[PDB]
Image 1 (tube, chains in turn orange, blue):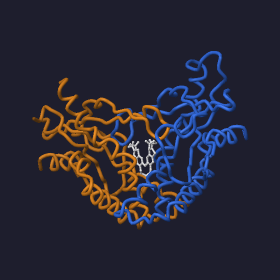
Image 2 (tube, rainbow over the protein chains, first blue to last red):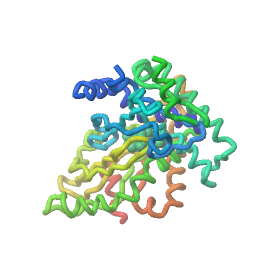
Image 3 (cartoon, helix red, strand yellow):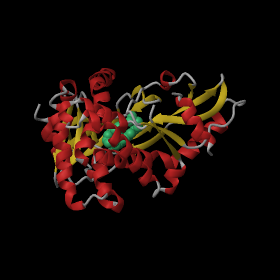
Amino acid sequence: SVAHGLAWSYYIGYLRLILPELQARIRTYNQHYLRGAVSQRLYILLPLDCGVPDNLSMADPNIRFLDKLPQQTADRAGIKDRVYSNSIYELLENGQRAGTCVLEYATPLQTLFAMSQYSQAGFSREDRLEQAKLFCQTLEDILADAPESQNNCRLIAYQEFSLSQEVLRHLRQE
Amino acid sequence: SVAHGLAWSYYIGYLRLILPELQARIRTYNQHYNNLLRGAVSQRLYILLPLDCGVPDNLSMADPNIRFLDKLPQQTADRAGIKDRVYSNSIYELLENGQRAGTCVLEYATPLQTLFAMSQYSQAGFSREDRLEQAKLFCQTLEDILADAPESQNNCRLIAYQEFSLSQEVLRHLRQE
Ligand SMILES: COc1cc2sc(C(=O)CCC(=O)O)cc2cc1OCCCOc1cc2sc(C(=O)CCC(=O)O)cc2cc1OC
């Protein structure tokens, strides 16, 4: 139930607010500059081990930062012009650019990791994998009822390895 | 359980990352961006915790005595693959009988809106009548976590309430310091 609430909050508090505006941001980026073009959809990394690093090129050198997408702003809960920033990455395969996409980790998975570390959270490391799977499954179930959000994102769940090959397999499915 | 996880995530995923850098941003605003003739913006993030889980996006709509003054200088950090993820926060003037009674950084705890949404959607398996108990649990859990994070606890103030003057609610907390 910790993961059930986290998935509902990740959707209500974030995905619901950025995914309807994402297509236009990507088109605007591609207009100023097929595979050369940044692919559509937010690619969401879901490591079931709940390991969320801040730098992607550290996780896999074949994932290289290209540019920041133009930021989205909106008045949110008293924050005037709350800023939504997203990053574009190149995916390399044997020294060649094989794909370009908007990529990030689902940050609530780091909450599961931290809760399993802190005694006061009353959350055991033995329950973390089941909770990570439930977070992913709940997010999939919600997105199945939100067509605008579902078509604007791709869920990349995995257990450990090549992170770029994991992303490319999803990118090549289209 | 839903609210227990939401409070832990609001701390781990947000407060833990902005509260250690807040003091410096307020001091910078006061030294270089604040109107020369104005009083200093108070320290600490004032977090609104409406137990009814009603989270509007515009504060002057909730109470006309809460007026937007300026945005604090933004904080940036590489976060989970987002290069220079931006943290923006807003400064408000609190009016009492037409005049300035206080100036502070203010916002709603957005996870409370998740409780409201879940109580509405059938697929969330969260009964309409469960909202208040979960809102109270969110606030209590957040208070418990902050009691173990010294810097963070000193960089924020929790404003929990049931409905009314929202500006008077904030001023009572501002004046306690
Ligand atoms: C209100 O609920 C959420 C809001 C956001 S905003 C967000 C991002 O902007 C993605 C990048 C990041 O985590 O910095 C993720 C989430 C997840 C949310 O739900 C997960 C459960 C609650 O935990 C968090 C609460 C907040 S509140 C927050 C804010 O930026 C405050 C203003 C706002 O919500 O727009 C970030 C988080 C991040 C959280 O977990 C990662």
